[PDB]
Image (cartoon, coloured by chain):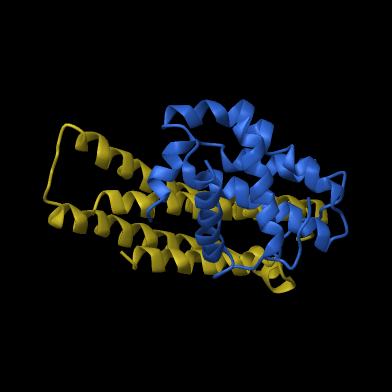
């Protein structure tokens, strides 16, 4: 329910910063800023989809899985879910920069269910989604 | 506050250059100078971080203690994750070295794409783990 919408607007927003755009709102806003604080630690002393991989329409599900596994290999926290959202965004903007985009909808359904099935359980334990805003809100 | 973060920014900045996987980098990756350097910047990051939790434990004066045998234990483990990510980054480049050594110095693209996969996963988890900390180093201090 919730997680489908949260992915929608977060991907929505990640298009804007690359001169692009395609198809309780305090959650969506805080997560948008968290990904910005996160990304200007990234692109600060890094580079963008520059440390990239070889992304085809057929390997994207493999690289998504490899990265997402290793991201949560040893626990789940809020800072890593922001990375999970940031990574999912890095997928979509590398797509249009590499001439794919209906992949985005796949990536969008590669983040929702993963929250629904394997992340939903940890979310409600540490206070639900409204716990994320309480810890990253007035900051 | 902004010094273990600077040492971390020096670890990430160096890793950033290894993520370029340049001809320069690949030649370097067959030596032990890149993994030796990573341990230094990591052992510096953990040093500045360990000395900064102690620095807080001094001016940290409110001391509600029924939950602080839970507080500091949550953060002594949340720094345990940061040193873990930085150890993993180092190991992922030891495996790359030992893998090309079994290819007589040669290196396939299947290997470099796989290494780039792990480096991205680690950069993300590194930054995210450092984020879950710097916020938890403001519930400690405030």
Q: Quadrant of the N terminus of chain A?
A: top right
Q: Quadrant of the C terminus of chain A?
A: bottom left
Quarter of the image holding residue A105? top right
Q: Residue at x 54, y 45 (%)?
A: A25
Chain B drawing hue = yellow
Q: Is residue B8 left or right of residue A91?
A: left
| Whether residue B125 can be seen here | no
| Whether residue A117 can be seen here | yes
Q: Residue at x 50, y 29 (%)?
A: A122
Q: Position of residue A132 (x, y in %)?
A: 45, 42
Of residues A45 and B17, the one nearer the viewer is: A45
Q: Position of residue B140 (x, y in %)?
A: 25, 49
Of residues A108 and B60, the one nearer the viewer is: A108
Q: Position of residue A44 (x, y in %)?
A: 55, 70
Chain A drawing hue = blue
- Compared to A87, does B67 lie above or below? above
Q: Is residue B123 left or right of residue B20?
A: left
Q: Residue at x 21, y 34 (%)?
A: B67
């Amino acid at each position: 329910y919730d997680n489908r919408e949260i992915v929608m607007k977060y991907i929505h927003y990640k298009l804007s910063q690359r001169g692009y755009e395609w198809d309780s709102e305090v959650v969506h806003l805080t997560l948008r800023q968290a990904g910005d604080d996160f990304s200007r630690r990234y692109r600060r002393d890094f580079a963008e989809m520059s440390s990239q991989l070889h992304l085809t329409p057929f390997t994207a599900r493999g690289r998504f899985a490899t990265v997402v596994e290793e991201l949560f290999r040893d626990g789940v926290n809020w800072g890593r879910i922001v990375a999970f959202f940031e990574f999912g965004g890095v997928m979509c903007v590398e797509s249009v920069n590499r001439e794919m985009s209906p992949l985005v909808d796949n990536i969008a359904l590669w983040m929702t269910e993963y929250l629904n099935r394997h992340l939903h359980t940890w979310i409600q334990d540490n206070g639900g989604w409204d716990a994320f805003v309480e810890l990253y809100g007035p900051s | 506050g902004q010094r273990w973060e600077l040492a971390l920014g020096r670890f990430l900045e160096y890793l950033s250059w290894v993520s370029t996987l340049s001809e320069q980098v690949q030649e370097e990756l067959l030596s032990s100078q890149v993994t030796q350097e990573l341990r230094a910047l990591m052992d510096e990051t953990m040093k500045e971080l360990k000395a900064y939790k102690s620095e807080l434990e001094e001016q940290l004066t409110p001391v509600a203690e029924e939950t602080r045998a839970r507080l500091s234990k949550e953060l002594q483990a949340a720094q345990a994750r940061l040193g873990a990510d930085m150890e993993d980054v180092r190991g992922r480049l030891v495996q790359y070295r030992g893998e090309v050594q079994a290819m007589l110095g040669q290196s396939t693209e299947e290997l470099r794409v796989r290494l780039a996969s792990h480096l991205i996963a680690l950069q993300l988890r590194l930054i995210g783990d450092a984020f879950d900390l710097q916020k938890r180093l403001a519930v400690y201090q405030a």
